[PDB]
Picture (cartoon, rainbow, N blue to C red):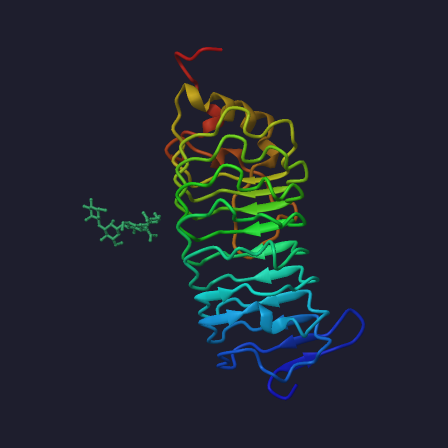
Length: 266
Ligand SMILES: *[C@@H]1O[C@H](CO)[C@@H](O[C@@H]2O[C@H](CO)[C@@H](O[C@@H]3O[C@H](CO)[C@@H](O)[C@H](O[C@@H]4O[C@H](CO)[C@@H](O)[C@H](O)[C@@H]4O)[C@@H]3O)[C@H](O)[C@H]2NC(C)=O)[C@H](O)[C@H]1NC(C)=O
């Protein structure tokens, strides 16, 4: 209570423990805390089990806290949001068995180089997954099979060279897909299925414009109003779409949706 800032009234009880050189969870915290901020601390190691006493905790922010090892012990039955962004995790924590009600997971800007087969098992309620700014080169097929309710997916600014065929199949609620600034060369045929994807970011990739890019070319033409350019700190309020941002070899004068495709089968 005295160490961190507390704010109550209606909605819930938010506890702010940011920037306090904390190396562990303060033993002095309101048992009814619903939102806990532990950002900007020195949590090289942290154990989720230490939060079990706080039964109403629905949001936990452990971002920018030098997090290196996250111990996933017991169970936090009502935790809905977990922010682990801007930390030093080299492996994705396996959270399914501990955070069954999780809807938002942010592990952006960590040190991930790959994702395991078990990755998202058990996170059936997941709605937002952010993995921007890591160094992923490829994704396991079936990565998103445990998360059919996904609405937002961010794989921006990684090192992806290709996407698994079928990655989006089954995601009938997907509204935002961020894939900008990777090393993507093509899009698997039928990748987007028959689902309407309102916000897609595909710029900053060295698209290879050959006959294999024709599926993507047609999709871009049919979805020109759903393609956008990312702008830090700004909501896609009504931001003007810009299909021309998706370019062959990331060359400004050669947008993929204008690629002629000379010498290519129908
Ligand atoms: C994941 O993706 C990251 C983003 O592309 C990537 O980071 C880039 O890495 C390259 C290679 O290390 C960086 O390029 C070098 O930059 C330094 C300083 O800016 C230059 O001195 C250096 O000189 C050139 O090196 C060439 C060989 O690579 C050589 O042929 C040239 O003659 C010349 O000597 C490079 O230009 C680049 O800046 C990084 N980008 C950023 C924004 O950090 C990661 O390496 C990649 N991760 C993995 C695992 O591949």
